Image (cartoon, rainbow, N blue to C red; front, side, top):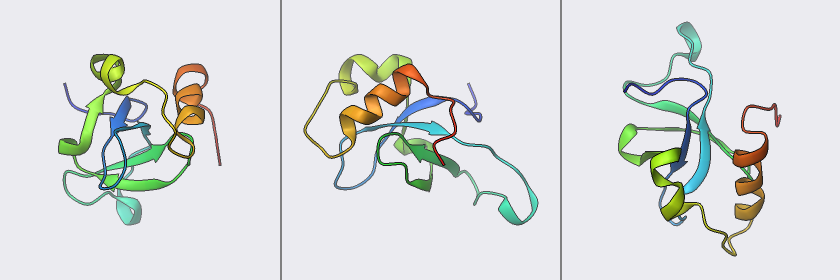
Length: 91
């Protein structure tokens, strides 16, 4: 049940609804994440951030609740990405 690069999630942060996202690559050395933090890419708006598991909701279990369209900027485009090409390069 450990998170791994490529898992799809809804990621939660302050001021936004639970947001379609993915776990990015995890490496060591000078790009090693902080302890118990994961590199997250947000679909639709395309930021990256480190988040901990408490803010990460596995996509399949949560999509019925969180994966409905809304008016937030980039949200519905994010929904398109997570559904139709979640593992693409967006950079």
